[PDB]
């Protein structure tokens, strides 16, 4: 079921085997249950949001109850919280800027130009 | 002044941005602000083409200011999704933090990290 799991999240089988080798995802039974899908989605999205594979591994250590890689979690949380807070602030200002730019467009006054579907994408 | 401008984040990168038409062909404070803008925008996941299109408005370039509306819609949706996700991740990290013993300790309070 590696192919369907690869298509579902999704990433190529190479990166799935790569995460299996890194230990980011557990060894499947003789396969790949729903938990593996949620975990893989977690890894993928976290990596998309700027987190390194090492940090993701450290977080997944909490899930697997690995005491070793859960060492010094306090400082880690503090650092990541600072980073992500600044990032959030920046993105919010940028978003307000983008909206402000959108209002200055003529189409913003047109009813048929209203972004209906794009809302739930 | 490109050496002084180089403190901001290097010279080849500056010449590269000049060749792309991202920055005018140097000495100015406005150029410093613009360069910082480009850099930080790139740090936050925006491509050079997107940043170029946004800077098309500052340069009053009619050509690349076309279809700005759909661009804004797209970027706003994407960045909104990102913001939601990041907020939730932050609350997660705060949960984890509060689950630590050090979180109850006064000397372990992150005072300096606040304004970094």
Image (cartoon, coloured by chain):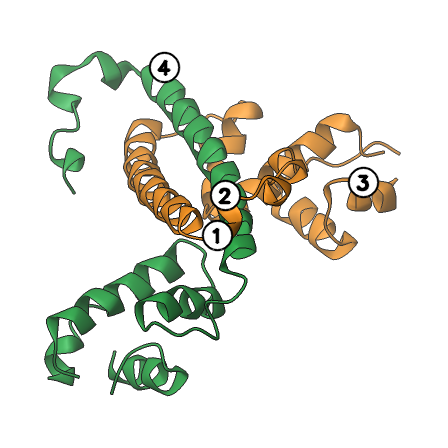
Chain colours: A orange, B green
Instruction: Indicate which label's residue lies in the foreground, 3 or 2.
Output: 2
Q: Position of residue A59 (x, y in %)?
A: 48, 32
Q: Nearer the viewer, residue B62 or B100?
A: B62
Residue tagged 2: A109
Q: Alpha-carbon distance for marks 1 and 3?
A: 45 Å
Taking the spot 51% from the left edge, 67% from the top edge, the residue there is B66
Q: Position of residue B9 (x, y in %)?
A: 24, 69
Which image quadrant: the N terminus of chain A? top right
Taking the spot 15% from the left edge, 76% from the top edge, the residue there is B5
Q: Nearer the viewer, residue B49 or A16?
A: B49
Instruction: Please check whether the numbered discs 1 and 3 fall on a single chain.
Output: yes
Quadrant hosting residue B86: top left
Q: Which mark is on residue B99? A: 4
Q: Position of residue A95 (x, y in %)?
A: 39, 44
Instruction: Indicate which label's residue lies in the foreground, 2 or 4.
Output: 2
Q: Earlier in the sequence, mark 1 or mark 3?
A: 3
Instruction: Please check whether the numbered discs 3 and 4 fall on a single chain.
Output: no
Residue tagged 1: A106
Instruction: Please check whether the numbered discs 2 and 4 fall on a single chain.
Output: no
Q: Alpha-carbon distance for marks 3 and 2?
A: 44 Å
| Marks 3,2: beta carbons within 8 A | no
């Amino acid at each position: 079921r590696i192919g369907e799991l690869a298509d579902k999240c999704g990433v190529n089988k190479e990166t799935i085997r790569y995460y299996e080798r890194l230990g980011l995802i557990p060894e499947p039974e003789r396969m790949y249950s729903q938990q593996t899908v949620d975990r893989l989605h977690f890894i993928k999205r976290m990596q998309e949001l700027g987190f390194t594979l090492n940090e993701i591994d450290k977080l997944l250590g909490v899930v697997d109850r690995d005491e070793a890689k859960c060492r010094d979690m306090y400082d880690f949380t503090i650092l990541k919280i600072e980073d992500i807070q600044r990032k959030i602030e920046d993105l919010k200002r940028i978003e307000r800027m983008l909206m402000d730019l959108k209002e200055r467009c003529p189409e913003n006054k047109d009813i048929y130009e209203c972004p209906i579907i794009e809302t739930l994408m």
